[PDB]
Amino acid sequence: LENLKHIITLGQVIHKRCEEMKYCKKQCRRLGHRVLGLIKPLEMLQDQGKRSVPSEKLTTAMNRFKAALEEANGEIEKFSNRSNICRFLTASQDKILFKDVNRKLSDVWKELSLLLQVEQRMPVSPISQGASWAQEDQQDADEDRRAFQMLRRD
Image 1: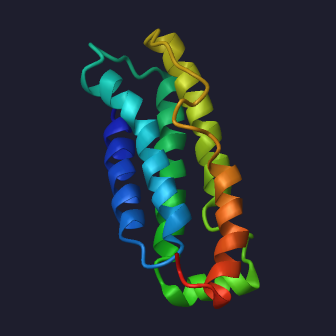
Image 2 (image 1 turned 135 degrees about the horizontal axis):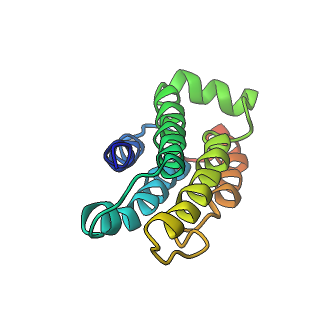
């Protein structure tokens, strides 16, 4: 739970920072809104889930989680500077802003949720949050870089 408060809170920041992102908001907004969805179920477990023993594995997941977040938050933060975005799109740093995160951040929930199902016995679904972040991230990536180029920042 020690990490949960860091993940949930960060889930709000990653969401607040992305919500206020001056660039690539399309994907950014998703990262946070999607991230929030990952912290959402926890809110029912960690907050009102009646107890929650953070085993060595559980904490390790939430650890990877809280850390994985810093990636999204860091990616959204490092991208906050338009100078970085404009130079990342045309240059294509990684083809997608927080793709590596949706990729790492995702696996975390897979290990965090699957662990919780054991430690807390809480029923979970295949990332109900919608692990399609990557599919939309790239769709918005190739579209973003190609959008801001000459198309109005929709």
